[PDB]
Image (cartoon, rainbow, N blue to C red):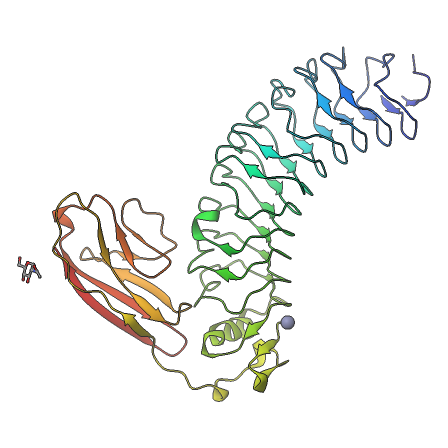
Length: 391
Ligand SMILES: *[C@@H]1O[C@H](CO)[C@@H](O)[C@H](O)[C@H]1NC(C)=O
Ligand SMILES: [Zn+2]
């Protein structure tokens, strides 16, 4: 029995383009597809979807939806996709989607949502796509927001004005990440730590001014990387070098400073060739393609350790530090322990870690860490090292 202002087929009901204030009651039991878009629905009550055990696609987008009650989606063991975009939701309805291991797609794009609470989507761990796009009024994301989503492949946090990248370490199977249209000032290694399966990353129009040393080294399956339209002047030495599957990169519309620090990039471009980034400065090279720069225009020498490490006598328990500040800040820094273990700002080791400065940090150090440590700095022109022991 088909409802009034709708169009039924076969298991497909179409009730679009009608001034409907609430969901119609007379819904057939055997329906998979259900379109309730371009209507004026404000509230979604508990158990509004009765006996819909065949429902795979439910579409509640482009409405004035303001409230989704507790257990609104009970009795839906077939639900695959759910659309709620272009609505007026001020939060995410955590309790609504109660026990749904069948839900694969979720679209909360373009709502006035203010935050993503701890364990927001824990009730739907089988998610594959999650669209949180155009959340212009978003003000805070929980560190434990994206817990439970171990099967998520796609995530959209575009057009949200994010100051910092939220915690994504929980998402071990992520393959595509949209972060465009944000205010992500600088990019850190730890931002992407634990995203080895990530293939595409989009940081277009992100107001990105700096990328830290070894910021991407963890993303060892990255193929597409869009840093177009940002405030990048330079990139650290050999940022992309270790990423071996990288084949589409957009570097255009950044104020590229073409000094000695760009030569690794011009060489990488000249080599890798994604198949158009131009020098914005200095005036001598303005509008020259970065990947066509030969080395003759530049005078470059080994990197200079402005602040080399001095020897330290330390107590067992207290903090410790061995400095390695350099000219420039883009020059790559590798440390070397007395073990023979090499280290980098990209590394994910507890306690001991190389801060963005280039300095090697400690916390709760032991006496058995005694030995000679060496800072190994490299740029486009050569290698330079300085070494000092700690006790
Ligand atoms: C640290 O101790 C070693 C000997 O154990 C000594 O060579 C060194 O001068 C000491 N450093 C300072 C300045 O206390
Ligand atoms: Zn350009």
